[PDB]
Amino acid sequence: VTCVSQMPVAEGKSLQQTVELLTKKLEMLGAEKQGTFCVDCETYHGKLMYVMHYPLSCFALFENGPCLIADTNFDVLMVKLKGFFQSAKASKIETRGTRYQYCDFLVKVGTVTMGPSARGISVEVEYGDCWSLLLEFLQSFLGSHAPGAPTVFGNAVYGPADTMIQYMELFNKI
Amino acid sequence: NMMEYLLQGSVLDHSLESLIHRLRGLCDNMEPETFLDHEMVFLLKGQQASPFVLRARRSMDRAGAPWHLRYLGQPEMGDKNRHALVRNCVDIATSENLTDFLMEMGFRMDHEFVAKGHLFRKGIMKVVVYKIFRILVPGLSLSYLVELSVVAPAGQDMVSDDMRNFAEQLKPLVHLEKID
Amino acid sequence: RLSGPQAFDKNEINSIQSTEGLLEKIIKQAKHIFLRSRTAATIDSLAS
Amino acid sequence: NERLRALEDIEREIGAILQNAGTAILELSKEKRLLDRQAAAFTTSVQHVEAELSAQIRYLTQVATGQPHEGSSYSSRKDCQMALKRVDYARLKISDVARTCEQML
Image 1 (cartoon, chains in turn cyan, brown, red, orange):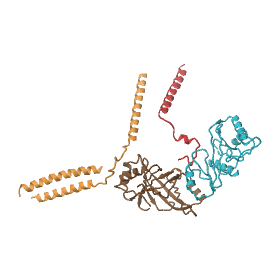
Image 2 (cartoon, one colour):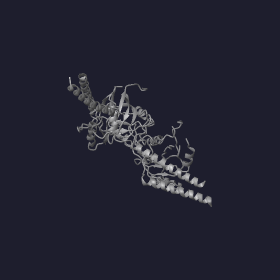
Image 3 (cartoon, chains in turn yellow, orange, blue, cyan):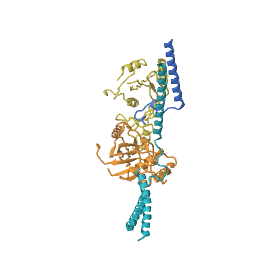
Image 4 (tube, helix red, strand yellow):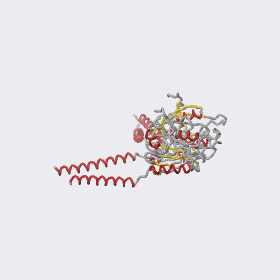
């Protein structure tokens, strides 16, 4: 499926402390480690970028995005497109973290991109629309979460770029 | 980073066998094939006064193949007796995403052309024969085109002499050269 | 190049190419002896 | 295909033209009927053989640069060899099964 990411602004102890608490809860759930899948999407201008893992940097800027350019295709195109887009002043940062896989699942914690940011959680599903199981698993993870806003009224058929659209919306929201 | 050594080729429309058999025999490959695609040039340059071409060549006879696009221009004056080409930068695309992004970012279709012919390859080289038509979107100059081209990193222009020798090998039929 | 449009994280990036040579023949011989042993065990249990 | 037969016919015609020229010279120098027509035919055949040789030499010169037509479908040859080997192994196994059945009955 394509589970959107949320921005739970935790407080009290620390941002890193809340991230460690979420990781400890996930480990208590019984999820093993599956490498560090650091996602990266930098805005530009109304252009964008993407490094979500996958050797394809697919910048879904607008009009749902192509999401087909290679890891170096869009990058070389933007590097050669000097003078066309002169809005490179406002920079953009990206998060990182780990990636666990409990069973047919995935979890990604979105840390501080440039330093100001919350712990952005993100999950996926097995086949795909099919939100009963997703919510039943999310409620056992934490409390206030699951904003939603998917590509409703589409049938798309499990749009993979929907994750990128949710990430872009979250990055613009903070 | 990457570069190209594309050479221009133009053969008479009637001289087809002396090209196909020679290329199939001298050194191209085993089990040759053909192709069919149509190009869509674009340009978006308001004040820069430098229209960048984005050839979204989509193979109509392909099963949803990506719209492999290439950027070419500003031939570098190397004077290395080579094909006198410039740097290249390929870029894949999705289904109908090339037109979608061209409409989103804003582009102007300079022209539309279609190509059709046989395919050939080499070790670090590539030669292609095809014919261009002048027809509407639903579907000619009477002159085939030998697309002897090389795309590779900068290196030391070692493939230039190899391409020159390969062109001299097919001298009785055609005579490749550069272009302006 | 299909990794462009259909961006696969680690499935096709690893399935595009893999090792071969002696490992394949070894696996085939292992499967052969395993099938032979299973058939022999079934035949022996039937005869017993 | 046809060029080989063409060259063979050209060589045979050159030989026949030489023989006809010799015979015409002999008949004309023996004593003094059809010697004039014979000499005319011999000269015409010699000119035709020369023209055919010049045309064959002025061929398209296919490659003249390297070993052409590289690759004689070796993959298909190997595939056919493997198919024949499969057929032979199947025949051997079938003969073994038939011998076992004959020993059974």
